[PDB]
Image (tube, rainbow over all chains, first blue to last red; front, side):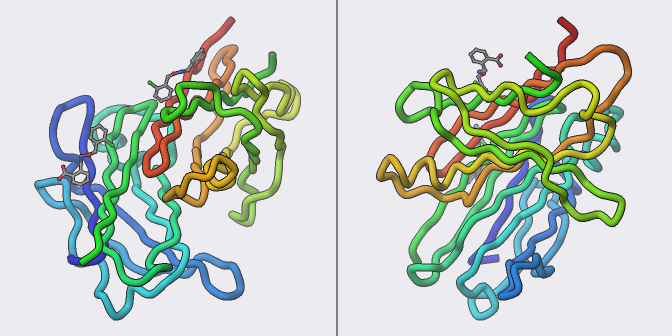
Length: 117
Length: 117
Ligand SMILES: O=C(O)c1ccccc1/C=N/OCc1ccccc1Cl
Ligand SMILES: O=C(O)c1ccccc1/C=N\OCc1ccccc1Cl
């Protein structure tokens, strides 16, 4: 809710991208991707409540946005399997992260907004 | 000049992104990512010759663009560890895949151009 939020928009419809599955992973000491949190975007395109300040420790995180499943519910066969956002988090102390993604069938854009509480 | 080309642009400097490492992987039957091809973008930001028509069979591929090292070499603090483009390669008719990426320190945009020249 506070420390990690994901927002997804649809560049074809000019709308939030609703009901998009998002899976977050964190790299473990053995270099594997351990499951960290998951959820689905709301009617606003936003996904809150993935983690807490306590659990969102330093590490390398991967946010996987299940874009192919999204387009495959709207009649479009898209190019990408998903959109992946991989970043180191909290290495200089806690921050709040918003990961935004803008989706088209053959393209996506992503940006991050990082704030210090 | 092959079935798969990668082009990388720099949105801060308004230039090709030169000397960016690019690693391509193919998904194996056990769902792991197997190294497939790699190189570094040229002075034009392009990477040709990754694969051949013979070897680039249908399957799921991941193109990892090593953006963090690119920004670090410029003295710029970036957000992402790398940019990842994951897609299924499709044989329906003669097709050439160009993966293009536009890089900023906290953002990237990617698109696919799938043509038949
Ligand atoms: O693709 C090509 O053959 C090509 C050839 C010459 C010069 C540029 C490009 C791709 N540049 O495309 C721009 C772009 C790429 C990715 C995301 C957003 C944007 Cl605006
Ligand atoms: O809307 C919000 O509340 C928001 C807040 C913080 C960060 C991102 C966004 C979504 N918008 O930014 C994403 C975007 C806009 C235009 C072009 C490309 C892209 Cl990726």
